[PDB]
Amino acid sequence: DCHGTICHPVNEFCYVATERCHPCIEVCNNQTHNYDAFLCAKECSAYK
C-alpha cells in the first residue's frame, strides 16, 4: 500500500489505484471532480 508510506490519518488516504496518498477532502466533497461517495465512506469518513 502506497509503497510503505503512511499518509496523514485524517486528511489523506492511501489511494491504491496510484499507490499514493490523496487528500480526503477531494474524494468527500461532492462539488469536486474527484468526488467518490464509496471511497469517501470507506477510506475517509470515520477518521474526520
Image: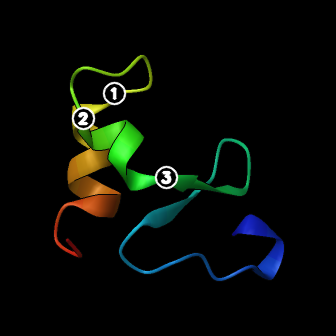
Which residue does the image show at 20% across and 52% down from the upper left?
Answer: 41
Q: Is residue 19 above or below residue 31?
A: below
Using residue 1 as the reference point, say whether residue 8 is left or right of it: left
Which residue does the image show at 40% across and 39% down from the upper left?
Answer: 26
Q: Mark 3 points at which residue?
A: 23
Q: Residues within 10 Å of mark 3 (few under 14, many from 20)?
A: some
Percent coordinates x, y for residue 30 in the rendering: 21, 25
Look at label 1 and name its amino acid: Tyr
Using residue 30 as the reference point, say whether residue 12 is left or right of it: right
- Residue 29 is marked as 2
Sequence-wise, the earlier of marks 1 and 3 is 3
Using residue 7 as the reference point, say whether residue 36 is left or right of it: left
Q: Distance between the residues labelled 2 and 3?
A: 11 Å
- Could you say whether the residue bearing mark 1 is in a helix, strand or loop? loop
Mark 1 or 2: in front is 2
Whether the residues at callouts 1 and 2 have beta carbons within 8 Å, the answer is yes
- Could you say whether the residue bearing mark 2 is in a helix, strand or loop? loop
- Could you say whether the residue bearing mark 3 is in a helix, strand or loop? strand
Look at label 2 and name its amino acid: Asn
Look at label 3 and name its amino acid: Pro
Q: Is residue 48 above or below residue 43?
A: below
Percent coordinates x, y for residue 29 in the rendering: 24, 35
- Residue 47 is marked as none
Q: How far apart are marks 1 and 3 (CA)?
A: 11 Å
Q: Residues within 10 Å of mark 1 (few under 14, many from 20)?
A: some
Q: How far apart are marks 1 and 2 (CA)?
A: 6 Å
Percent coordinates x, y for residue 3 in the rendering: 83, 71
- Residue 35 is marked as 1
Q: Is residue 32 above or below residue 46?
A: above
